[PDB]
Image: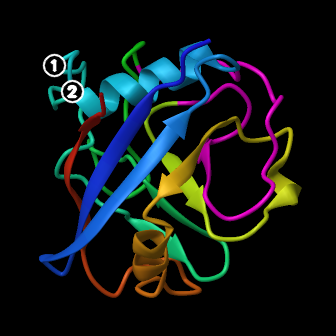
Amino acid sequence: MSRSKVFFDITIGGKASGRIVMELYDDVVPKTAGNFRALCTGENGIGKSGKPLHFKGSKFHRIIPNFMIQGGDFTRGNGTGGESIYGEKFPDENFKEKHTGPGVLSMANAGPNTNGSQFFLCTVKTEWLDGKHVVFGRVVEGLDVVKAVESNGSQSGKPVKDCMIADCGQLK
């Protein structure tokens, strides 16, 4: 049915770097899409973690050149944290959409049925993740902002500086 539109305003080392706009596939993965939408708006307030269920102020803690940029750990900030609005973990909804190219928005996980709040934005086609990570959206404006964050990644995954989601929300 009706696809949601959300955004990130990004800063890099504290400097304003632009807005990423994402379209979500509510029609294909309504549960997965709704979780990310509510985390952009912050509407479910404080999580079991004791931290806001909100991407605002979080960072891309893992960034790999010619692969993807990854974020959403607003509880630990290191890839070990994160929390869904549903209460920490939720199953893989379905694997209908594929990792077909740059701009694909997909859930990070620690194996089957481990979805939380961590997600990634692909900078290349990553077909080896099909059937393993739930794809739920795509970048529709600001892919250049994505490339800018990418240039701050390392093979190791560690960023060379803080790439933050300074602001976020739902459009329209």
Q: In which quarter of the image is the N terminus?
A: top right
Q: Where is residue 18 in the image (x, y as percent from the top left)?
A: 27, 68
Magenta residues, start to end: 88-115
Q: Position of residue 72 (x, y in %)?
A: 38, 46
Q: Which residue corresponds to mark 1?
A: 45
Q: How is the image coloured?
A: rainbow
What amino acid type is highlighted by mark number 2? Gly
Relative to 140, 39 lies left or right:
left
Q: Are marks 1 and 2 in contact (CB under 8 Å)?
A: yes
What amino acid type is highlighted by mark number 1? Gly
Q: Does the magenta stretch include residue 112?
A: yes
Q: Which of marks 1 and 2 is in front?
A: 2
Q: Nearer the viewer, residue 18 or 152?
A: 18
- Residue drawn at (70%, 20%) of the image: 28
- Residue drawn at (20%, 18%) of the image: 43
Element on which disc 2 rests: loop
- Residue drawn at (22%, 15%) of the image: 44
Q: Which residue corresponds to mark 2?
A: 42
- Residue drawn at (43%, 64%) of the image: 142
Q: Magenta region, mostly helix, strand or loop? A: loop
Name which quarter of the figure residue 110 lies in.
top right
Q: How far apart are marks 1 and 2 (CA)?
A: 6 Å
Extreme front residue here? 172
Position of residue 145 relative to residue 96, above or below, is: below
Element on which disc 1 rests: loop
How many labels were placed on the picture?
2
